[PDB]
Image (tube, helix red, strand yellow):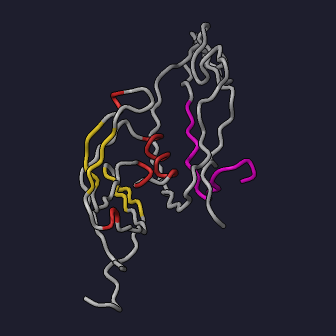
Amino acid sequence: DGVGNASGDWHCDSTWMGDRVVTKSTRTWVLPSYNNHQYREIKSGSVDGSNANAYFGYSTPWGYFDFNRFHSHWSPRDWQRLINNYWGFRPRSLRVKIFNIQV
Amino acid sequence: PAMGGFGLKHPPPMMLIKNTPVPGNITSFSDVPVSSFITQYSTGQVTVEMEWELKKENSKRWNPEIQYTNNYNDPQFVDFAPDSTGEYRSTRPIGTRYLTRPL
């Protein structure tokens, strides 16, 4: 929409409803311009005495978002409530939003 | 009340049980009341059912809380269980306040 209008709002919360718990997490991120807009071939020979260290690869201009840690979604008090009262847990659904961009 | 608990204008009512007098052999009439009775005792089962209303915690505290736990160093018996003779053991008094709230 516009320069003066906000794209989204802050949501950080936990809701417990019987057999289901919903977790919401909001963070602020910074992105560098990596490689000065270029793709680079990357490689290694044996290091620290080991050939298992050797590799051939590519480095890229892009960056990525990673959420595979429990502390990213769970407060320390919320984690204590689950470990104390339940036999088991499993994941069901994921939703992601990116907003309020500034260059 | 000073000891603790709920003060009630109309409390759950007194329940009273007695064994009916059964007389011993009487062969003659008297105005004076009988003082001779057969010796007797009674036995049975009693069931009590109670309903309780609960108030849920709504805390926003980030850090973990204090909790009652079974925690013993080098235990020689299990607490709240029968012993080798069959006598129940209850070593610790237990209160209700482990959760915390702001004023």
Q: Residue at x 39, y 40 (%)?
A: A86
Q: Is residue A99 left or right of residue B55?
A: left
Q: Residue at x 29, y 37 (%)?
A: A55
Is A72 colored magenta in this rendering?
A: no
Where residue A88 appears, as percent x and y from the top left, is 34, 38
State whether residue B12 appears in this view.
yes
Q: Vertical placement of B48 versus A72: above or below?
A: above
Query: Which one is in front, B85 or B79?
Result: B79
Q: Which region is colored magenta?
A: B1-17
Q: Residue at x 33, y 28 (%)?
A: A52
Quarter of the C terminus of chain A within the rendering? bottom left
Q: Vertical placement of B52 versus A27: above or below?
A: above
Quarter of the N terminus of chain A within the rendering? bottom left
Q: Main secondary structure of the magenta part?
A: loop
Q: Residue at x 28, y 47 (%)?
A: A91
Q: Vertical placement of A82 versus A66: above or below?
A: above
Q: Residue furthest top?
A: B85
Quadrant of the rendered image containing residue A6: bottom left
Q: Is residue B24 left or right of residue A9?
A: right
Query: Which one is in front, A57 or A65?
Result: A57
Query: Which one is in front, A16 or A60?
Result: A60
Where residue A97 appears, as percent x and y from the top left, is 28, 68
Q: Vertical placement of A15 versus A87: above or below?
A: below
Where residue B82 appears, as percent x and y from the top left, is 58, 16
Where residue A61 appears, as percent x and y from the top left, is 28, 62
Query: Which one is in front, A20 or A101?
Result: A101
Q: Is residue B30 left or right of residue B22?
A: right
State whether residue B31 appears in this view.
no
